[PDB]
Structure formats: structure tokens, C-alpha cells
Image (spheres, rainbow, N blue to C red):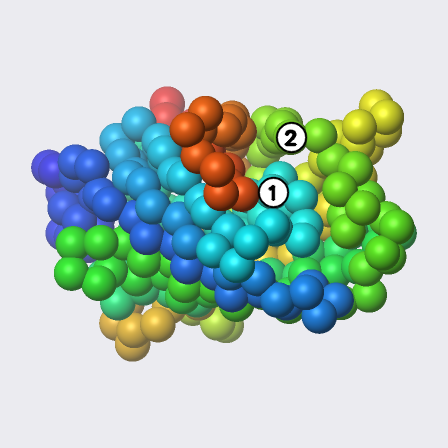
């Protein structure tokens, strides 16, 4: 809405109210090719995303929880006193590229590249995923992960040379036997457009995700409720 900085006002304008989301992923893990399509809606005022994903090629060859971070940080709630640090909305509507390498400890790695931008009124996240060096009997290709997701906090830093941001963080996936599978994430984001963006001071995003199933859905799928809030810079 009403912010003294017109660059902040421009990005906030695009995310006031509920915004529809489309997610489209094409993936290849150890030569198992698959596609995922997701639909839902984001409400940046509360940091809230509701999405349902479907594997459109049949059975997903990897566990759904390993794709949560890959399958839209512009819907994060930034407190008023931090809105000058919201890179993700400032890059819109032209969008940004989000690249990751995700290393699964003692297993394979995912490399992802995504473009996040508006098509009309719809926020689209278009992802390519390549996964290599997985063990056919490991926790990933073996489907030994529980269907759930732990809350965590992630630190965001500016990358002033790329006019973007970078982040590195660990996700712990629960294994069915009570142990944990570590997923080390390395992330960078860069704007698609040439115009100015907001480069943030160091801060973190607090994330909580709930995974569920649609009782009427026969296709392989995941229902996701995610909350993401920015924090780590104090008001006064």
C-alpha cells in the first residue's frame, strides 16, 4: 500500500490481495524423467501459500518432500520496517532466476534452474531439475522419507556483483526409521530485467510447511501449505 519509498510501493502493489500461482517442473533424476504441475494461490500479506501439485507423468520417482524447496519467495511476508529489503518483489513483474544445487548427504544432487515471473495476473514458476549420482537403494530413490517437513530459518545475503542474492542452508528430511537425511542447499537469485532492484541487508526467512493429501485425488500428488516470514532486523 502506503510506503514513502515509491520502489517499495511498486512491488507491494503487485502482491496486495490473493495472487494465483502456476508451477511447472520438468525433471530428470538418474534418467527417470517426470513432470509436475501445481496450482494454487499466494497471499503475501500473511506470508501464506496454498498449492496442490500433481505428477503428470505417473508415479513421482523421488519423495515429494525433497521437492518442496524447489516447487516462490516473493510471497514471503516482510514486516513494514523491512520492506526495503524485499528483493523478490522488487524484481517483479519481469521476474528473477532462482538457481540451486542441492546435495543429499551420502547420495546424489539436484541442480535446478527456475524462472519466476508474472504472466498476466498469474505468478508462474517454471523449473528445470536435473538429478545425478543417486543410489538406487538410497533414501531418495528408495522412498524412505517420511511425508512431512520441519520448520527452519534461512539466511539471505546480498550478492552485489550479480545484483542479486545468495543463500546457503540445510534441510533435514525425516527417514522412516527415525534418522535424518541432510539436504545442503546452495542458492542464487538474479533479476531477469535490467531495472533496479532492492538489495537486502542480511536477514532470515522463517519457514513452516504442512504436507497433506487430497482424499479424492487418485493421481500422485502433494498438497502444501507454506508460511514464510522475514525477520532478523529490529525496528526500534
Camera-side residue: 71 or 46? 71
Residue located at (82% from left, 65% from top): 133
The x, y position of residue 77, in whole percent, is: 34, 34
Instruction: Determine whether 201 is above or below 134 in the image.
Output: above
Is residue 205 shown to the viewer in this render?
A: no
Between the residue at mark 2 and the residue at mark 1, the CA separation in whole angstroms equals 7 Å
Q: Earlier in the sequence, mark 2 or mark 1?
A: 1
In the picture, the disc for residue 147 is 2
Q: Are marks 2 and 1 in contact (CB under 8 Å)?
A: yes
Quadrant of the frame with the N terminus:
top left
Residue located at (53% from left, 43% from top): 220
Q: Which residue is mark 1?
A: 64
Instruction: Determine whether 206 is above or below 104 in the image.
Output: above
Instruction: Determine whether 229 is above or below 91 in the image.
Output: above
Q: Residue furthest bottom?
A: 194
For this view, does 211 lie left or right of residue 33? left
The x, y position of residue 40, in whole percent, is: 32, 41
The x, y position of residue 10, in whole percent, is: 15, 52
Residue located at (51% from left, 65% from top): 26
Instruction: Determine whether 109 is above or below 78 in the image.
Output: below
Label 1 element class: helix
Residue located at (41% from left, 28% from top): 216
How many neighbours does mark 1 have within 10 angstroms: few (below 14), some (14-19), or many (20 or more)?
many
Amino acid at each position: 500500500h502506503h510506503h514513502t519509498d515509491p520502489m517499495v510501493s511498486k512491488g507491494e502493489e503487485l502482491f496486495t490481495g490473493v495472487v494465483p500461482i502456476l508451477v511447472e517442473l520438468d525433471g530428470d533424476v538418474n534418467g527417470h524423467k517426470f513432470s509436475v504441475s501445481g496450482e494454487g494461490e499466494g497471499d503475501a500479506t500473511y506470508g501464506k501459500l496454498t498449492l496442490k501439485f500433481i505428477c503428470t507423468t505417473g508415479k513421482l520417482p523421488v519423495p515429494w518432500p525433497t521437492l518442496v524447496t524447489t516447487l516462490v519467495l516473493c510471497f514471503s511476508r516482510y514486516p513494514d520496517h523491512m520492506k526495503q529489503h524485499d528483493f523478490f518483489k522488487s524484481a517483479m513483474p519481469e521476474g528473477y532466476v532462482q538457481e540451486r544445487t542441492i546435495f543429499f548427504k551420502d547420495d546424489g544432487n539436484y541442480k535446478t534452474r527456475a524462472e519466476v515471473k508474472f504472466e498476466g495476473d498469474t505468478l508462474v514458476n517454471r523449473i528445470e531439475l536435473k538429478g545425478i549420482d543417486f543410489k538406487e537403494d538410497g533414501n531418495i530413490l528408495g522412498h524412505k522419507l517420511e511425508y512431512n517437513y520441519n520448520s527452519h530459518n534461512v539466511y539471505i545475503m546480498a550478492d552485489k556483483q550479480k545484483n542479486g542474492i545468495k543463500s546457503n542452508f540445510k534441510i533435514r528430511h525425516n527417514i522412516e526409521d527415525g534418522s535424518v537425511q541432510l539436504a545442503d542447499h546452495y542458492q542464487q537469485n538474479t533479476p531477469i530485467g535490467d531495472g533496479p532492484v532492492l538489495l537486502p541487508d542480511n536477514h532470515y526467512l522463517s519457514t513452516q510447511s504442512k504436507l497433506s493429501k487430497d482424499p479424492n485425488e487418485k493421481r500422485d500428488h502433494m498438497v502444501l501449505l507454506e508460511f514464510v516470514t522475514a525477520a532478523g532486523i529490529t525496528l526500534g
